[PDB]
Image (cartoon, rainbow over all chains, first blue to last red):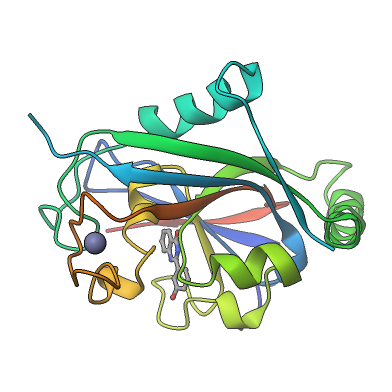
Length: 47
Length: 161
Ligand SMILES: O=c1[nH]c(-c2cccc(O)c2)nc2ccccc12
Ligand SMILES: [Zn+2]
């Protein structure tokens, strides 16, 4: 894995074209995330 | 040391996790190529992931980050889709779960939009889709996503062109 930018603990990807997209985030240390919930699902075919 | 506890659909905790999953679906610029064509999910099960050792690893790091950032961990709840979900829940996140070719460098990626993470359940770009039918838009096969507690600390803001 890469390192975080100097003096930072993560990167935020802010959308600048698609006005409906929410942010995405990157961490460079696995210890900075804990998998709280496991969600089992299907995608639904639109009607 | 990981145990999985099923949440009842009557539990307020099930309901708040389901609402975050459903309400953060969006349309994708690939027309559904990677993740499939859908506006909502059928939630089959929500399980709490309990591992004392992995939780302590997380809270140790969280305290280190907080102390470097005026006692602010900047903790978020974010989605993660991966073909490695089984390894992650048993052994924790590590370098093997990184997206080497990601837009922001080789690290572990998380999304506010559940539908963004859904694009990675079967691999980068949806891979070849579900193992049974080779369908990235499979409506039959069961998928799994993680809803994760993530320490951001001081985050570098990248605007996306
Ligand atoms: O949920 C995600 N998983 C992944 C992912 C997970 C495992 C391996 C990998 O190469 C990418 N990448 C993302 C990128 C942007 C937004 C969300 C994700
Ligand atoms: Zn299938």
